[PDB]
Amino acid sequence: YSGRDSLIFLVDASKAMFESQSEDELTPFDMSIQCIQSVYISKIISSDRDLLAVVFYGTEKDKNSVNFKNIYVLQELDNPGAKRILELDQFKGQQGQKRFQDMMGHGSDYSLSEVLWVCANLFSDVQFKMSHKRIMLFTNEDNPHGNDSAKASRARTKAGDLRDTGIFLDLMHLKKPGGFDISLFYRDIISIAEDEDLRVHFEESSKLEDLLRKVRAKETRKRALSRLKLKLNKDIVISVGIYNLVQKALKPPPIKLYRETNEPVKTKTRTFNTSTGGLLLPSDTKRSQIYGSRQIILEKEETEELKRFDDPGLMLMGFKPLVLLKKHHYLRPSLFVYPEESLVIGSSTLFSALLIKCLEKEVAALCRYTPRRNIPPYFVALVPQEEELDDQKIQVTPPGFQLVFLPFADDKRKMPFTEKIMATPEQVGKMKAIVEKLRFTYRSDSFENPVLQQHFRNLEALALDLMEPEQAVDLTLPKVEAMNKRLGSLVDEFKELVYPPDYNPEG
Amino acid sequence: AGSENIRVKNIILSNKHDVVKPAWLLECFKTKSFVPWQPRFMIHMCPSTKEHFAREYDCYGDSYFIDTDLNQLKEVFSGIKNSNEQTPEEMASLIADLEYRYSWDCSPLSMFRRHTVYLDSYAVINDLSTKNEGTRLAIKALELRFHGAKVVSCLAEGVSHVIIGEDHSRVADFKAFRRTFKRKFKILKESWVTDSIDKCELQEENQYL
Amino acid sequence: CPGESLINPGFKSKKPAGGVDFD
Amino acid sequence: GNKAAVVLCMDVGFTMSNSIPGIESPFEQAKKVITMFVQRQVFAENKDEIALVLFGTDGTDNPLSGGDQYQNITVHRHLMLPDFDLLEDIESKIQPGSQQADFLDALIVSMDVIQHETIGKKFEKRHIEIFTDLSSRFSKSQLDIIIHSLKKCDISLQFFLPFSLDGPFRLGGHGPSFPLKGITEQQKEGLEIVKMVMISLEGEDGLDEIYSFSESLRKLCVFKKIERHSIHWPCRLTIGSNLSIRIAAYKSILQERVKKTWTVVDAKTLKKEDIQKETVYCLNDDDETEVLKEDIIQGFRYGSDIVPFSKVDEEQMKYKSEGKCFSVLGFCKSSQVQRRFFMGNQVLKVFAARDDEAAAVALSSLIHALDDLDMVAIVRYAYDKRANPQVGVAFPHIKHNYECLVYVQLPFMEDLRQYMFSSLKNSKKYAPTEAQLNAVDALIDSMSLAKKDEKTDTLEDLFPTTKIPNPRFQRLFQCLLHRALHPREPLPPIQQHIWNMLNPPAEVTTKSQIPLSKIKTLFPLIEA
DNA sequence: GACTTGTACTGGAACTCACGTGAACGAATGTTTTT
DNA sequence: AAAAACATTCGTTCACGTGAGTTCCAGTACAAGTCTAGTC
């Protein structure tokens, strides 16, 4: 997947979209607007480089590059922004609906072929590279063209050519009184027609639930950190790539702005002599260190040469049993090593053989790792990782090597001497019971970074001019009430068994 | 800022700036002058501005040196939210105190506030389970209450006025109760209030005894 | 294909964070 | 504050100068070890007193030399801060002596120096290191007095020998050193006496204090008795609202950086004040208008739109959480937690509070219960109110000596990256062959770094990289010393012993040539 | 005589890590004050 | 003589600013094939 993602929101403007089947129920148009706003907000955070467009069809007013009738392109393909979200929300309320009806129009004929043509032209307009081109249709009419067969055939053929081109069309059918049925007219328009969605739907499309689910997390396309060479010997060399399957999430860096006008400012750093004031070239300056009354002078090139032992890469050492790799000897987050095959041919076969033999013998490859030029070498262990997939054939553990850094002698700190005090079996049993009471299943993605979530919520509230920020539920809190309810009195009897009557564990 | 959005709330949290309702600019444009601020326009106060307006203005929109108009009085009253810390008897006593202090008894209504009124709407006196609702007596009592009379459903010793309809069977009982009580309440008829309302004045009770 | 997120194609729709749910 | 006094006893007699062809002289090895010691002491800017005494020197400079006793012993440097003068003396103007001496006299002189110079300042620890070949006659009449004096003074003692208790010999090459049959009867007696004194002073563990120059060059053992202990972080592990256990956490593992930092100085004049750095903010305009710092405001990007975000506003809306929190979110099977997901840059070792029987026994019970149930505790960790909260895993760690919890941070949902990798096992194009698999198996067998010892039925590590000191610090110290001593000279090449210690034993290297050639011929690899 | 396509090059933008610095901050040390 | 409060210290974390190696993709030069206007 190389390129960007383009999405077009086709929203029907027919009278069927402006009606309340029951009280306390947002109209289909309001639901579509809410879904569009949620998608825009999610794309703002997850991937702001994507392209989103909003097109309305069936309105009296028209605005298209083709100058068609009853089609309005509210927003052409462009990166998402707060202004677009505000414009979309302008029609959110009942007053917004009235404003949209007055300024845009209603109760106008249309043609599916025309809107498909407009969407195709919009896609062609973009000058970037689109990995995925997608259209979403928000309509609640089963047969837009039932009176005229020619229009229906034209729409069908236009959809067929659109699918052949590479555009993926989805139908976000909304609730309608009689009931929505894909099999009637839209069966041949959707690029993929799931056999399940062949009956009549009396409720909203299930995809709206997914669309309305906001996601606050920066999603990044796969990108190899570095392509290095694993050297079994001087001549035997294979090409591998290193990825960071786990990486810390940092809030976007702050930006300096001019207070009066709120526009980006340019920051410039300069170095000058305290006596002359003229600019100093890097060669003019020198690096020095002070040790008491002695001063040592070195240049930048010498400083770089200081930390330089071997060229970048993974110099393979002997193999080590996995038992000798202590689980508590953790220094740095681990990396993933996968054969590249784009630099040296045949490396994939050797990598696969090495992985298979390492799994069979339960050993790990000890190597000297040098990521970049002029950097001290480190010691790493590549442990095999076989492919693992959960139900319904979805991969969860990619196959390759897991690279774990082994700490040096200086990286370990000595602990103070402590006398070991053993616990009587009764206390151990009581704690085993308590732990069993507090048993729970842990998944790698069961928690959310509260700081990042709160920062994103505040940023969204400020951008969208919201009344107040959306408070973020802290999943990291211990929810102590539930624990107290579950444990009952176990804490009390344990404390009376172990803690002396006068201990006061508070000071 | 005319809308108290998140930015306005954040500025409110900090006490280093003053917020003014957008009507201030419109008022300046209409008068084409640099009119000073008023509590009505501003929704927040800096400590310096708070001290400045504390001397000139009061806790509410009302000021000391500059008089107030009907619109200003309405705006000030709208500022106060509610006051339910007292009791009806306290309100009656306070109202009487103000009327006496300012001699406001000449108003078209409220003269009956100083006098308690009882009605013979019960077949048995001092009984709350024998109401005679559905006659001119109920409407007369309601009108008396509207005009400011304090309608009392219990025949306490503090009653000063009693209204008896066409039924004069219990006149002897009322006279006996009046004699027994230390303070005597004049016997009055329903026609008295009907005549008085048109005149809007307390007609002499001698002709309606 | 199954479980794909309709917002970011190519990335599986991550399940909502649940936290701690005692058995 | 914390302080330590170290006296280095160096053998200088002619017997040490002897060497076999192809073998580094013991004097050179001792000089290298002491050079590393002094380099670390001086370049680390630690307040440790270093003194140097040499026995076997032709001259005699010793306070106790009076009386025709303890002759040929020179107190080269008394207790004082290490300085470049000491390094210059060690490296350049120190030469072997033609007269032998008894190391017991050196021991007595070192003890006298420690006693006389210790009174001046407080000293938390006192250490003595003796480098000798044990190839000289000695008198056994001073054993009882020596033992009593050492016990009374309570000063640690370390011995360094040319050999430890058949390819080429390399310094710190993780291989045999000083092959057997090269030990003389006098050397045997010296080994016996050093072993007996070490056992008496310390016991069985003291038997491990007799290191070798090659081993000490790549083991960091010289600083074992001088390294301090990191401060403790105290908190209270709370399961619910009521149960709480006072605990102290230390940083068991933490990446070690260089404390000293380079600073730019003008080449013409080497003065800090000469070079000044200024930052100026200018708008994106032709006039390049300049603005003041107070004028600048903070904002964030919102997908092609910039929204102002004042620092005070950020603080007001910042996520606030009570600091110094160590709470147990829950307990989960150890299988669920995997080493692949560990994050952070540190590992915490959590013991009970200092001198607290109740907390100690409670933590012991928790650790034992977790170990028996094969469970770990998912916990919330916060260093202080200004530190972002973290979700981590604490798991038991029980040893014959001490038992404690080990805490390592765990990832959030944002941190995880969802990358899809094509399967390799089912890849027909890249599928291997039986001959290739056999060759790879032979290669793996020939390059095993662990030996299955049947005498104890255990695994012996031949290349324990965890004990190797970081070569970066040694290289930096060597180069700094070379530049200081020789201002006009190119930086020296990396020391040979560093490369030897950064490489596997020659046995595996020479035992894996044929398998590697077989892999090369069988596997076709071409650049593309 | 111009267009249009495929190759290759170049440079911008984001990513990641190392280095250097400044400010908060919680707890231990040494000194001072009081009864 | 014994207990409590304040100045100072110091490792630790967070965050800013700079530099430098890598990957990816957008803009542009350059060779080169193809097609048109025009004629005969």
Image (tube, coloured by chain):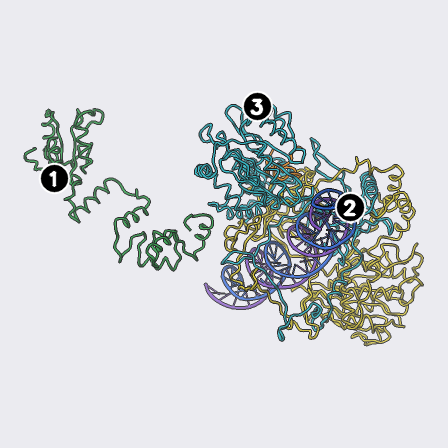
Chain colours: A cyan, B green, C orange, D yellow, E purple, F blue
Determine the chain carrying the residue at label 2.
A
Comparing A400 with D169, the one in front is: A400
Q: Is residue B197 above or below residue D326?
A: above
Q: Is residue A58 above or below residue F33?
A: above
Q: Position of residue B158 (x, y in %)?
A: 16, 37
Kindly identify the amino acid type of the residue bearing the numbered disc 2.
Leu
Q: Which label was assigned to residue A382? A: 2
Residue D470 quadrant: bottom right
B104 relative position to A149: left or right: left
| Gap between marks 1 and 2 measured at Cα | 107 Å
Residue under pointer 1 = B201
Residue under pointer 3 = A200
Residue mark closest to the camera, 2 vs 3: 3
Residue A46 quadrant: top right
One can see residue B110 in this view: yes
Determine the chain carrying the residue at label 3.
A
